[PDB]
Image (tube, coloured by chain):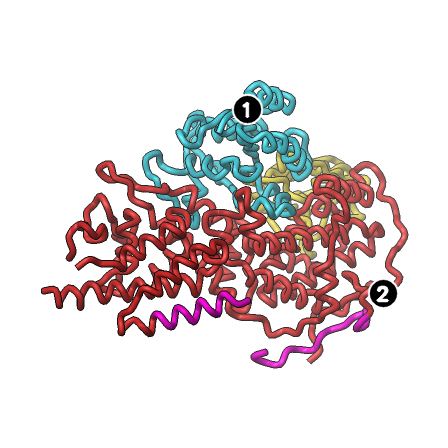
Chain colours: A cyan, B yellow, C red
Amino acid sequence: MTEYKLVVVGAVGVGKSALTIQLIQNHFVDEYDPTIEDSYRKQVVIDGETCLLDILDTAGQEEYSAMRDQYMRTGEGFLCVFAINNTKSFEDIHHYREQIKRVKDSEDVPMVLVGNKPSRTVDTKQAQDLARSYGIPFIETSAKTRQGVDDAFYTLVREIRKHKE
Amino acid sequence: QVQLVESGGGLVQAGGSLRLSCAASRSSFTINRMGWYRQAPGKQRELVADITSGGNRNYADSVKGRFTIARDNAKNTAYLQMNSLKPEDTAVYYCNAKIHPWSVADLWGQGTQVTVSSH
Amino acid sequence: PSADVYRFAEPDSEENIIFEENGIPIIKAGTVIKLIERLTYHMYADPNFVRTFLTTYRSFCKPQELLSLIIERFEIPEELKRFRKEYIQPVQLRVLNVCRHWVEHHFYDFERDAYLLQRMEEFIGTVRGKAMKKWVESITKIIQRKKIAFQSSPPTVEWHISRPGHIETFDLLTLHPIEIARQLTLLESDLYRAVQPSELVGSVWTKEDKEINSPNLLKMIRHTTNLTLWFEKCIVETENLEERVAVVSRIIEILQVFQELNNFNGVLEVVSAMNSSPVYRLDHTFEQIPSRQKKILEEAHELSEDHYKKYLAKLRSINPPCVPFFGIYLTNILKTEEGNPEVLKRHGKELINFSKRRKVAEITGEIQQYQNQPYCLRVESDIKRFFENLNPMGNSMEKEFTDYLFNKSLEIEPRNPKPLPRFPKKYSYPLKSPGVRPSN
């Protein structure tokens, strides 16, 4: 079956890990063990096609800033995550995207902008406009209620498919 | 677990042309270097041409001016346009991939017979 | 035992304590009252729980609160001869053992909160048991001490072009590659061994106070980052192709010795630089690297593939001394804490989820296992100082500097079809390496 190598990127504390864990967990099981393969690889069906998602989430290593190229180079598509209560994490997005394009030596890399849900300081319209300027989808999530989590990863899988076609 | 699938090849008259094609099956990122090697009866396997994802190429002296290699980075596919073929070009031709610029491990295709017949 | 004027005597039920089902019972969850009861249980000793509780409790109980609860645990209200012998005496001893472990192994709680220590000293002054005089004196001695602040012959230091003492000529190609690797391994081993569990539990290196709560960890990560960036800068600032090839080759030889020393932090410092956008794209440079050195870099990079699968196996297979790559522990601690609930609920009651704390303590325990054994290698003060003072970014911010490196890459090997310029040499001395075989 087809495997998709996804990489999650973004500033510290924006919910990269909660998104990844909420995607991988079966819905009503609340016990995560990050030391095993089933914690980052998941078989799903998307638009009728069954595939294997391999998610690289390096949350907690943000201070190793010279390793980002190494981690990004492993990926086919990128979830660029910011926290909607954290304006600086939204301002960082441009730099992550430029680093990814440089690593992939390409102007159109499959990518989705994710704004994950204190109170709101980044307007939905601002994030939609930023995503539009990049030519990529924007998705808001609430890792805590699980709202939008599947949509964010499946939309990235769709972007990867559109790119390969 | 990347696999290289070759197509093209076979029998052709001396003076004629063939295009070999190579497509990598299951890869997450651009293969650093794709190329073709060939092995004639009695000889070692030798480079024919290769090309990096940055477009830098090498050609064997014996095919320069006759053979052209090209690739599509986004697709991890490559092709070899072989013109003005000579009986000395008869060989098994192999697609080759080096994943990284420091790669020494080879990924090989299964090998494609090319037989160039004369008059 | 006692009636319920002693909160710890309430009977176990599914709504105050849960055990792991997969020697000693292992607690999966409990009210803080039940956790402290089992921490000081009358029926058996539990040194592993004492260790993991005192390592992790601050995520669910404040230090002042813990002291209040253990004093409450100790002050048991009263066959009564049987009760004293089989319940009061063993619980009280267990409490004193927790106090001793606390002041001996987690004295930072008292350094950060002087009133916590006053309360502890006041409590210990109340314990009069003739039996418990030895515990009393032992605890007092530790407190008084805390309030006050080569197995085998090492091999010969190796030298290349730079001679002993000529600090001002020290550089990547002029020091000996064996000795660069040795001295970076001593520096990185020291940085690794300095990281304490208090810098990790609660994921505090990711929070706003990270600079005060995780200084040794952050110092360690900043060294790794600076060395990776120095390798990149040495490569791309060497404009002449043959010189650059010699620089990349020498870094791979330093990598070979890092591997021989089981310094995986150093292995990754090199792997990360070679994966970086300014270095990875240098087709003309990598083309000239000897195949046997390509193979060394190839095997090192492969340790990182598939979520560090080969790295994890190799670490488990070698014998210390070693320097682990810390970033894996950081992600696993963070995901363990974020991916498991803080509390479990049972018939409406909240229980502290202790199993995820135990899992974090198992990670900090593995970190500690590798911190025991030092390297049998001799420090060289000038070389150590040279590396402690490396600052490849200069005065620049991260973005400006990484843009500089990439633009330098594009200058020294322009994109196709632009032609490859030739560039003048910069190194006056010979480029030939002495190799990485030691002398004797």
Residue A160 coordinates in the image, percent (x, y)? 55, 30
Please state the chain letter of the residue tagged with numbered disc 2 in the rendered image. C
Q: Amino acid at mark 2?
A: Pro
Residue pictured at 30% horizontal, 58% vertical: C39
Which residue in the protein does label 2 denote? C430
**Residue A80's image quarter?**
top right
Q: Quadrant of residue C432?
A: bottom right
> Label 1 marks which chain's residue?
A
Identified at 22% across, 43% down, the residue is: C15
Q: Magenta span has C211?
A: no
Give the image location of residue C234, x and y in percent.
Answer: 77, 53
Q: Tell me residue C255's x, y (percent).
A: 66, 61
Residue denoted by label 1: A138
Give the dominant element type of the magenta stretch: helix, strand or loop: loop
Q: Residues within 10 Å of mark 2 (few under 14, many from 20)?
A: few
Say above or below: C440 vs B47: below
Q: Secondary structure at mark 1?
A: strand
Please state the extent of the stretch shown in magenta in the rendering: C136-165
